Length: 99
Length: 99
Ligand SMILES: CC(C)CN(C[C@@H](O)[C@H](Cc1ccc(F)cc1)NC(=O)O[C@H]1[C@H]2CO[C@H]3OC[C@@H]1[C@H]3C2)S(=O)(=O)c1ccc2nc(NC3CC3)sc2c1
Image (cartoon, rainbow over all chains, first blue to last red; front, side, top):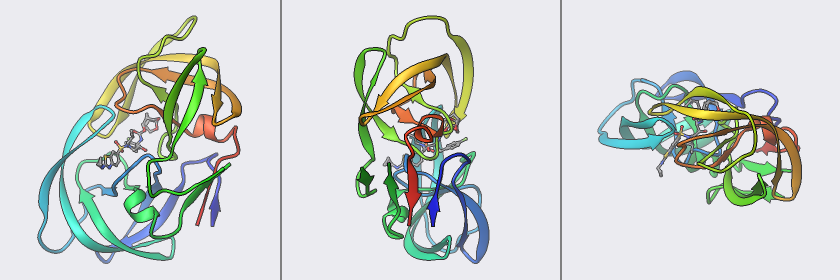
């Protein structure tokens, strides 16, 4: 779709067999989801944003469906205040900015 | 322009008579700039992001040029680790997401 920015650009995702809503976030390099149960091995990572840093679990090669488009990549899980789809996944679904 | 997301979507802005680079940030409701000298009255505001919250100076009705497009609106100034152009300004320049 085309999405305008009068409201938060929230879309439906499926990840780890679970449905969630997430922000299309061009200011996010990586994809970060609130506590969600994902399978398998992970590595602890500290990431930084406005306000400071959080500890996340890094999961690699995680399949995700983003508004009906398929991607696979790194998903970081931790105490983010918002589920954010970052550029690592947005590049796979052909998402662009236009003005 | 159209901007793809293989790299950070950074553009040149002019604000307060000064030139800066800033991220086109669809996950940002508001526009937040690192310490920059802006004229006139401001109101202290606490904003939240990943990692916690920052104190910012809120300036209203600030003109900004964003990659050659003119906007006017609220600009928050404070210890953000990145200059971010949020939806309050991106809607004025006709910025959309497309996939
Ligand atoms: C700040 C920006 C530069 C980065 N963030 C992406 C922004 O879009 C976030 C998303 C957000 C929304 C709401 C919220 F409560 C918290 C976060 N917006 C944001 O904080 O908005 C703030 C601010 C703007 O106005 C209002 O709107 C929402 C809220 C409020 C005040 S990030 O989430 O920290 C992030 C994400 C991925 C990532 N991957 C990395 N990978 C390593 C480096 C290579 S680093 C990294 C850092």
